[PDB]
Image (cartoon, rainbow over all chains, first blue to last red; front, top):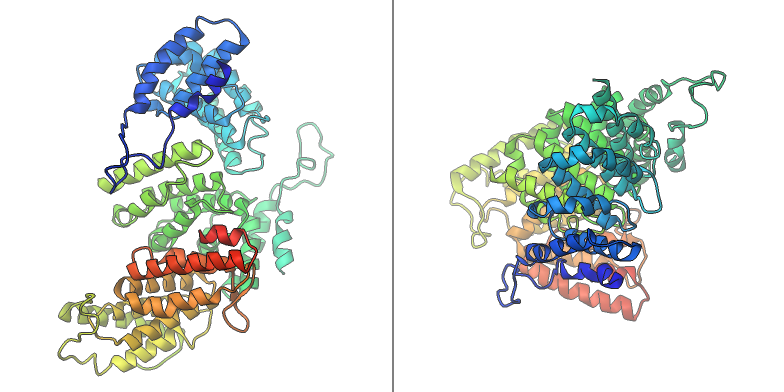
Length: 203
Length: 203
Length: 207
């Protein structure tokens, strides 16, 4: 099941060779609805199984499978599944592949844009996880840290000032290797993140 | 002069060991105004020399030197020099180091935020250069392409709709390896860039 | 309209000519691929066509390499004068193509570089065989037998081996004869640099 979970991304990917390309019409039996349909067939069972699972292996499998499915399906096109996805969504924020990282960061972006009760009830949990994402690591690429900055900004904008005032100093302190890392868009955006956090806390 | 130009970044950098750090006061003869002052001493002569130069080598030296100086000095803190910098600013958009790339992209961001006559008169020149920046290349990192996307958005926002309508299809067409590259923040932001360009052109 | 190489006098001459080309266009017409050689019956610009051709030729070429505005306006007025229905002979556009190619390989100045690219692309969309014969074939000939050589345009100025590939990528994007013959020649050079030469990046770039 672990191998199947890590290989389960294959079901949902682009082809670049078999779609209803302009010109050709005899290309294949193309159906664009495969992505969404597959998500609607996979997600629900996966999440029910994850909430009905105990150990390292099988829960890691469920997280990896649902993440590798959600990574290729557009996050904004899968809305009804977001609510039950929020637990595994928060789960998928710590694992080696930056692909699932960018995917789950995008999905929290869309969720906090749409959902706010989940964000308000789960901010005390999400914030240090985004902090660890923003920390330099063998798994946190410069782009991954940049995306953690973007999600930090988005969740600070969505969450009311009450919780955001309580989570200003940690972001201001645990970002020093991000506004001084190898790339500079990472540095510029970390400077901007620090400044925006400081101005939101001071006001 | 080429070696001096490529080494000329050293004059302006952070130290991380000799500044007026909190606590210590006997650290050094610290002056924070070194960056800006150095820019004001370097830029002008450099640009006059570049406009008074002919060949591969010496003009490349002037571009590299001014770029390696502007990269460490904050772009928004050097305002009066932007106007004469715009020619070498446009020049610095094609060279191997992604450091000068991010720096010059930031500087066009600040310029087009402030200057608009230069942007309107130079859009027909800048747009295909940003397109080549957005193209995958041995010198265009995924972050570099992301920044080219950001500058494309910023210049499309600043330039009136008249020129922006004329530069919609090229951005929509020459971005296919960016919303499908290895990273996905690059992919997500290229999808967003394509969508925003399409909605701006269609309206 | 007096011969002059001074930046001010020549620049004002060129920007004046930029309005007379528009007047001529509005009075007579513009190019079609069938009207590439057909001239309009009568005008006074025909009596001055030699003078404007000469002034544009000396404004782009036989001029210093530091001219950015002068050479940009030169190639722009060259292209605009080409844009008239059969008022310039294939010899004139051949000379203009040669000027564009020489000044684009000699100078790296991205002003003149991209302005010459624009002129060559407009000639390609208005003159298939002309550009394919003068510019494209020459550019395909600059590249040598072996990879990682200095493409010696002339005695001093040289371009990179990938410069020819980039120029090929620039135009021929909508020119049937150009693109087909370019694909054929690039395949020929791919085969040649794989057989008589030992290169990987050149084969990769060509394919």
